[PDB]
Image (spheres, helix red, strand yellow):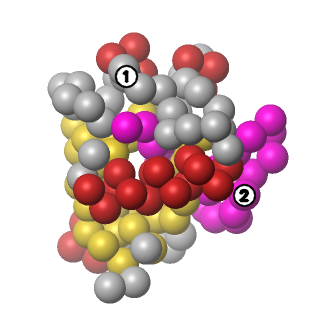
Amino acid sequence: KTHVQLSLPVLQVRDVLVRGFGDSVEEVLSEARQHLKDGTCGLVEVEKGVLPQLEQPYVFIKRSDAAPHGHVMVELVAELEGIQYGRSGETLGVLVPHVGEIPVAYRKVLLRK
């Protein structure tokens, strides 16, 4: 399928144990995609002071459309030293590995795969 229904666990930034996906735009987008597929991906909601607590490059989920079965359609955009790789809508949050942190909520998304 071109799209996959996912429910992403929303994590508090101070709980996150593994604060990024790797060391290059290409690696983080690769790893984020693999973790999304394996159900091992969390979401951190971006606010003042969140991003400096996480590791660059960042992977964002961004709204790609204006929501089948409650799932907002999103795509991946990566960011390194203020340059973004991809073009999309509003940020729903930053992706990180999920290694057993207790979520505060779930974000239903339809991921363009």
Q: At numbered mark 1, what does the secondary structure look like: helix, strand or loop?
A: loop
Say which residue appears at 26% left-offset and 56% top-offset.
38
| Residue 38 in sight here | yes
Main structural element of the magenta stretch: helix, strand or loop?
strand
**Disc 1 target residue:** 16
| Residue 62 in sight here | no
111 sits to left or right of 90: left
- Magenta segment range? 77-97
Residue kind at label 2, given as amino acid type = Tyr
Quarter of the view holding residue 104: top left
Where residue 62 sits in the image (x, y, percent)? 54, 57
What is the spatial separation of the Cα atoms under label 1 and label 2, in whole angstroms? Answer: 24 Å
102 sits to left or right of 44: left
Number of the label disc, if any, that sits on residue 86: none
Q: At numbered mark 2, what does the secondary structure look like: helix, strand or loop?
A: strand
Name the image quarter holding the C terminus.
bottom left
Name the image quarter holding the N terminus.
bottom left
Dot placed on the residue nearer the N-terminal end, 1 or 2: 1
Number of the label disc, if any, that sits on residue 85: 2
Say which residue appears at 30% left-offset and 73% top-offset.
4
Q: Nearer the viewer, residue 27 or 62?
A: 27
Is 88 in the magenta?
A: yes
Up-down relation of residue 24 to residue 70 (above or below): above
Say which residue appears at 59% left-offset and 50% top-offset.
27
Residue kind at label 1, given as amino acid type = Val
Q: Residues within 10 Å of mark 1 (few under 14, many from 20)?
A: many
